[PDB]
C-alpha cells in the first residue's frame, strides 16, 4: 500500500504549488519547509513549517477483487508571530485548503519490486476539519488539519 | 571575537529560508559576546597589568595565558631590558635577576585562540537554538507531545556547560 | 480446537513461501525467523522477525451439529533500520499480505488422541488491519497486523 | 587524532543513504576532538616541559606517558648527555647522577595510541548517536511508546563513561 | 585476546541469518577489548618492570600474576643469576640473598588464561547483547509490554558485574 | 567440577524436547564454573603453598580445608619428615617441634566435595533458569500479567544466595 | 538426615496424582540438606575435635551439643581414663583434674534429634512449596488476582525463619 508514497506525493504537490508561481493565489512561499520525515517540533528552526503525519490505513473488500482503502493524514502547521498569529494561520490554512481543493486528483508514483515506478492517482481526497492553538505560547502557534484519502490498490488477487 | 556568524548557523541548522529574522541575528550577536565572556577572555588587543613583586620571587604569571609578547616592563618606573627575562608559554615570565621590591608594570599583546575550535562553534549554535526556541522552561505539553528539559547548572543548560568548562579559564 | 495447530500451519506457510522461491514476488527472505513460541521482544536477536500471537477464540452454534469458530491472530513484524524503516515495513507488510491473499486456503494437520493427524483446511482467512510504530526508537520499528480466521471443527455432537 | 571517520560510523549504523548530512559530519568532527580531550591526551607532536628538581630525587615523570623519546634535556641551561640517564616506559626517566638543585627543561615527542582500540571507536559512535538523536533528555513519550534515559554522570551518559574511564589518564 | 568470536555468539544466540551485520561484529570486537581491560590484564607478551628494593625485603611481587618465567633480572645494572632466586606461582619471586638497596629491573613473559573460562565467554555474549539491543535505558513501553532495567553499577549492568568481579584482578 | 549436566537440568525442568538448545548447554557450562568459583574452591588437583613461620607458632592452616594429604613439606629448603607433624581435618597441620623462623613450602592434594550436595545442584539449576529466562530485570508486564523480581544482593538473586552462603568458604 | 520424604509431603499437600514429578522430588532432596545445614548440624556419625586447654580451666564444651558419648580423649598424646572426667548434657565435659597446658584431642559420637519434631517437618514442607510455586518474587498479577509476598530475611521467607531460629544452634 501507498502510505509513504502518497504522503510524499502530497508533500511534493504542496511544495510545487506553494512555491511562488501563484502570487495572487497563495498568500505564502514555503521555500521547501514542507516535509514528511522531519516533523518533531524540536526539528523545526524556521517558521512557517508544514509537517505531514501518516494515520491509520483501513481496507474494504468488494465482490470481485476490488477493494477500497482509506487513509488519514494529520497535518500540522507551525507558525510564529509577526502579525497576530490567528491571521497568519488563517492565511496558511486558506492556502493549503486551496491546494487541496483545486487542481487535479493527486498523482503518486508507486515504486515496484521489479524496479519500475507506475504513475497512479488517488481517487478522492478530502480535508475534513481544522483546529487552532489556544495561544498560550507566544510567539509560536499551531493549527491542526485532518485530511482523508480514498484510493484503490492494484487488483492484487485477480492479477495473481 | 566571532565564534559563529550567520553562515555557520545556516550550515548547522540547514536553513533554506532566504534570510534570518532579526531575532536570530541578534541572538547570534549576543551569543558571541556571552561565550567570549564566560570563558574569561576579553577582546582587548593590548593589555596593561600591575603586579606586586618581591626579591624572593622571580616567576610571574601574566593575566591572560594567551599573551604572545611583552612589549614593555618596568619596576618602580625603572625600565629593564629583554635580556633580563625570558617569556614562556601560558604567559609565564621568568626573571633572570632578583627584583627590587615593589610594583612592576607591564604591557603585552594578548592574541587569542586561532583557529576557533569546532566544539565552541557547536556550543554557540546550541545556545542560539536554546534562546530561539525558548527552551528555558521545565516542561511543555503542546498538543499531545511532551518534553522535560535539562537540570540546568549555573543557569546554563547542562549539555552546553561541559564544552565551556573544557575551556573555562581558571 | 485448532488454535495452536492453525498458528503452526500459518507459520509454516510463511516460512515456505517467503523462503526465496518467489524472488520477483516477495521482497524478502526470512531464513526461518518466523515463529510461534519465541515472541517476547527480548528473545529476538535478528531483524526482520515475524511473531505470531493467538487471540480469543469464539464459537457459534448452528441448527444440527454444525458450528462456526472464529480466531484472531495478532501478528507483530519487528524490523531494524537500514533504509528508512517505514519503507522496509511497507515491503514486509506487502509480502505477508500477498502470502495471506494468494495461494489456496490454509491447510493444517489436526493431531488426534488416537495418534493420527487429519489434514483439514481453514474455510476463510482474512487480514483486517495494519498499523505502524511512531518511530521514537531507532533503528528499531514495528508493524501490527490483525488477522481473522473462520473455521469449522469436526462435527462433534453428531459423530458422538 | 581521528578515532572514527564517516566510513566507521557508516559501518556501525549500517547507513545506505548515499551521504551523511552535515549534522552527522560535524558531530563526528566534534566527537573526535572531545574524546581526544577527555582522555587528557593532546594532539601536539613535540612537547616542552619544565620540572623542579632536587638532588635527593632521581626518578622524574614526564607529562604524557606515551612519550617515546627524549630529544633534549638540560639543567640550569647546562646540557647533559644521553649516557647520564635512562628512559623507561610510561615516560619515566631515571637519572644516573644526583642532579643539581633547580629547574630541568626537557623536550620530547609524545606519540600516542597505535592502533586506536575498537572500544574507543565504539564509544565515539555511541556519542555521535547520543547528540544526533538528541537523547540528552530524561524522558519522551511520542505517540504511545515511552523511554527513560540513563542517570548521566559528569553529564556524560553512564554507558559511555565506563569506556572513557578504562582509559582516562590520571 | 579473544574471549569470543562470531561463531561463539552465533551459538549463544542461535542465529540463522547467513551473516552478522557490521554492528554485531564491531560490538564483538569492542567487547573483547573492554573485557580484556576491565580485568586489568593486557595483551602484551613480554613485560619490563622496575621495582624499588631494600635489603630488609626479599619477597617481591611481579606486576601480573600470570607471569610464567623471568628472563632477565638486574640490580643497579649488576646482573644476577637464576640460582640466586626462586619463582613461585602468582608471580612471586623470593630472593635467596638480601639485595643491595636500590632499583631492580626485570623482564618476564606474562602468558595469560588458558583455556578462556566459559563464564567470561558468557559474560561477553551478554555484553554484546546489552549494547546491541540498546538496553542502556531505565524503562521502555513499546506497544503494551513494559520492562524496567537493572540498577547498573559502575555503569556496568549488575548481572554482568558479578562475573567480572569473580576474576577482577586486584 | 560438574555440579550439574544436561540430564540433571532435564530432570529438574521436565524437558521433553529431544535436545537442549546451545543456549542452555553453554549456560550450564558457565554455571558450573561460576558456582565453582564463588564458593572459593578451585579445580586444581595438586597445590603448592608458601607460609611464613615462627618458632612461637605450631598450628598452621592450609589454604584449602578439603586438603586430603600433605605430600611434601620443607623449611628453608630443609626437608622434614612425616613423624614431625600431624595433619587434622579442615587442613590443620600441627607441628610436633617448634620450627626455625622463615618460610615453609608445602605440597598437598586438595580433593573436594564428594558427593556433590543436592542443594548446590538445585541452586545451579535455578541460576541456569535465571539467565535463560532473562530474569535480570526489575519488572515485566507482557500482556496482562505482571511480576516484580527479587531484591538481588551482590547481583546474585537473593533466593540463590542463601544456598551459596551456607557453603561459601571463609 | 531426612526431615521429610515423599509421603510426608503427599500428606501435607493432599496430592492424589499417582506420582510426584522429578521437580518435587529433587526439591525435597535439596530441602532436607539445606535445613540440615542451616541448623548448623551435620550428618557425620563420629566427630574428632581438637581443643586448646589450660590448667585454670576444667569445663570444656564439645562442638555439637547432641554429642552422646566420648569415646577417646587424650592430652599431648597422653591418654586419660573415664574416671578422670564426667560428661553432662549439651556436650559439657567436666574434668576432675586440672589439665596440663596444651592441646586436647577427643573423639565422640554426635547422635542427633530423635524423633524429628513436627514443626521442622512442616517448615520443610513450606520450603518445598516455596521453591515449587516459585514464590521468590515480590508480586504477581496473573489475570485479575494479585498478591504481595513476605519481607524475606536472610533471603529466607519470614514465615519460615521463625521455626528455624527456634532451633538454630548457636
Image: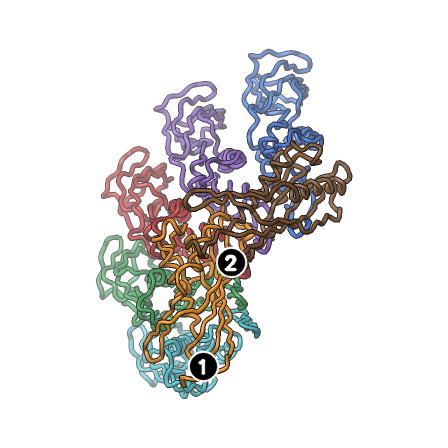
Chain colours: A brown, B blue, C orange, D purple, E red, F green, G cyan
Most foreground residue, F103 or C79: C79
Q: State the residue position of label 1.
A: G125
Give the vertical position of F27 relative to D139 (above or below). Answer: below
Residue F164 seen = no
**Label 1 to label 2: alpha-carbon separation:** 47 Å
The secondary element bearing badge 1 is classed as: helix
Most foreground residue, A41 or E79: A41
Tell me the crowding category of disc 2: few under 14, some 14 to 19, or many 20 or more residues within 10 angstroms, Cα based.
Answer: some
- Locate the N terminus of chain F by quadrant: bottom left
Give the vertical position of E74 relative to E87 (above or below). Answer: above
Q: State the residue position of label 2.
A: C144
Q: Quadrant of residue F64?
A: bottom left
Judge left or right: residue F21 versus residue B135: left
Q: Label 2 is found on which chain of the structure? A: C
Q: Where is residue A140 in the image (x, y as percent from the top left)?
A: 71, 42
Residue B6 seen = yes
Most foreground residue, E163 or D109: E163
Q: Label 1 is found on which chain of the structure? A: G
Q: Where is residue B126 in the image (x, y as percent from the top left)?
A: 62, 36
Amino acid at each position: 500500500d501507498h502510505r509513504t508514497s502518497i504522503a510524499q506525493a502530497l508533500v511534493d504537490r504542496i511544495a510545487q504549488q506553494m512555491d511562488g508561481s501563484q502570487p495572487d493565489e497563495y498568500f505564502n512561499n514555503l521555500y521547501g519547509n514542507v516535509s514528511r520525515q522531519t516533523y518533531k517540533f524540536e526539528e523545526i528552526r524556521e517558521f512557517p513549517y508544514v509537517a505531514v503525519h501518516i494515520g491509520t490505513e483501513t481496507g474494504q473488500y468488494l465482490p470481485s477483487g476490488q477493494q477500497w482503502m482509506f487513509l488519514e493524514l494529520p497535518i500540522l502547521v507551525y507558525d510564529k508571530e509577526k502579525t497576530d498569529i490567528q491571521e497568519q494561520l488563517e492565511k496558511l490554512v486558506a492556502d493549503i485548503k486551496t491546494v487541496i481543493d483545486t487542481g487535479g486528483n493527486l498523482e503518486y508514483t508507486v515504486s515496484k519490486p521489479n524496479g519500475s515506478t507506475f504513475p497512479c492517482e488517488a481517487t478522492d481526497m478530502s480535508i475534513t476539519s481544522v483546529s487552532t492553538d489556544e495561544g498560550l505560547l507566544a510567539p509560536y502557534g499551531l493549527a491542526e488539519i485532518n485530511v482523508t484519502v480514498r484510493y484503490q490498490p492494484p487488483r492484487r488477487s485477480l492479477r495473481r | 571575537m566571532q565564534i559563529i556568524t550567520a553562515e555557520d548557523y545556516r550550515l548547522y541548522g540547514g536553513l533554506k529560508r532566504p534570510e534570518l529574522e532579526s531575532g536570530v541575528e541578534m541572538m547570534i550577536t549576543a551569543a558571541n559576546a556571552l561565550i567570549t565572556s564566560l570563558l574569561g577572555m576579553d577582546d582587548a588587543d593590548a593589555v596593561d597589568q600591575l603586579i606586586n613583586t618581591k626579591p624572593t620571587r622571580k616567576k610571574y604569571f601574566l593575566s591572560s595565558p594567551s599573551a604572545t609578547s611583552v612589549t614593555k616592563m618596568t619596576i618602580n618606573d625603572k625600565e629593564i631590558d629583554p635580556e633580563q627575562y625570558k617569556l614562556y608559554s601560558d604567559g609565564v615570565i621568568l626573571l633572570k635577576f632578583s627584583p627590587p621590591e615593589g610594583y612592576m608594570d607591564v604591557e603585552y599583546t594578548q592574541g587569542g585562540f586561532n583557529p576557533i575550535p569546532e566544539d565552541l562553534k557547536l556550543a554557540a549554535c546550541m545556545l542560539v537554538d536554546h534562546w530561539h526556541k525558548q527552551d528555558y522552561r521545565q516542561a511543555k505539553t503542546i498538543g499531545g507531545e511532551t518534553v522535560t528539559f535539562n537540570n540546568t547548572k549555573s543557569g546554563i543548560p547542562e549539555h552546553i556547560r561541559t564544552i565551556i568548562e573544557v575551556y573555562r579559564r581558571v
